[PDB]
Image 1: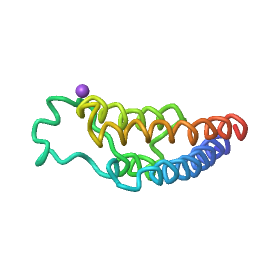
Image 2: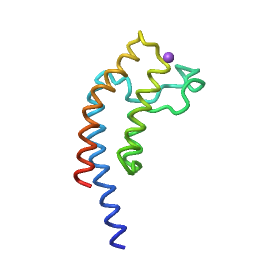
Image 3: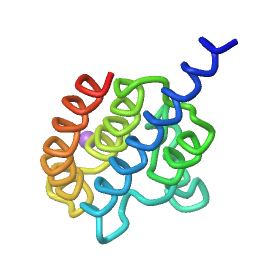
Length: 121
Ligand code: NA
């Protein structure tokens, strides 16, 4: 049907926009702290602590499968990256502080993405 096609085109354009968002967030992480999953072979107890691990490579995989149906879903995954880091790592660490800074800088990017998604429909 043409209605199905129109929904598919909308999902694709949302995907395009979420890609540009993902690239922008990732530019705020030049150290690449959040680029890849935590290795269960190097924080071996990680999964006793953190129930839903997340990272930018994992988000990129989901995005390439057009796996985010709306901005809220994408935001939830970004908030997991930040929130997991702030739980596992202490306040005094480089990791916790990098999560705080990414949250702050990512706020700006997400704030405009919400306006663009609303505006474009
Ligand atoms: Na903690």
